[PDB]
Amino acid sequence: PQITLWQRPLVTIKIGGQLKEALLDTGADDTVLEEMSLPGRWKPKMIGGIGGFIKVRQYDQILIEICGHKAIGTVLVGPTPVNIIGRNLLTQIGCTLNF
Amino acid sequence: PQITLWQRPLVTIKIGGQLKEALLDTGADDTVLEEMSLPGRWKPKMIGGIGGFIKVRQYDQILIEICGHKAIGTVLVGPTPVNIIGRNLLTQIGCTLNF
Ligand SMILES: O=C1N(Cc2ccccc2)[C@H](COc2ccccc2)[C@H](O)[C@@H](O)[C@@H](COc2ccccc2)N1Cc1ccccc1
Image 1 (spheres, each protein chain N blue to C red):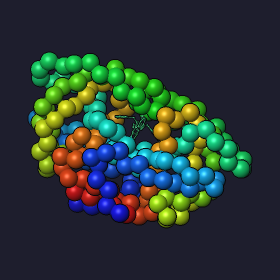
Image 2 (image 1 turned 120 degrees about the vertical axis):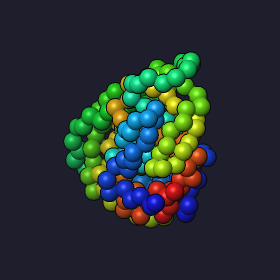
Image 3 (image 1 turned 180 degrees about the vertical axis):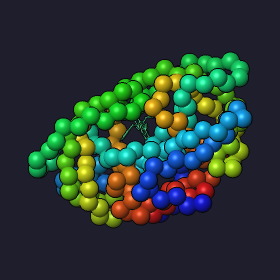
């Protein structure tokens, strides 16, 4: 798909067997989703941005399906305002920026 | 050009006669630059980030060249960790996400 940025680039993702709405975010190094439970061992992490830092739980080797393209990677879970797909998973689906 | 995401999508921008580095960020609705002096009057604006809200100053019709593309638009100045080019300017340079 070729996605215009007149609006926020929201897409559906399937994770944990759940369907969710997420933003394709090229400015984000990591993927961060709102509170949910994933199976596995997790590690605490602090991630910061505009507004300061938030504590998240880091889960590795998670499978996600973005618009139909499976991808595997680390996923951070915490009190984020919107589900964000960052560069660690966008590279796996082959997403590029073009102008 | 086509930009992949294995590295942060950093580009050089020219604003006020000077060169700065900035991040092409499809997750950011607006463009926010680190503290600097711009001409004119500014208006107040509050932006929600990952760690909360920050108050920034909004300047309108500012000329900024991004990778050789001249754009004119709204730029916010505030305590951001990095210069961020958001959708309001990414649309003026014809940027899309492709996968
Ligand atoms: O705070 C952020 N994050 C922080 C972050 C860091 C790592 C992983 C995920 C997120 C970066 C931006 O900041 C940084 C900080 C450090 C390094 C790189 C980018 C995203 O890239 C932006 O897209 C947007 C992401 O989060 C949100 C929150 C609410 C609604 C929509 C998006 N903003 C806020 C923002 C909003 C508007 C203009 C400018 C910046």
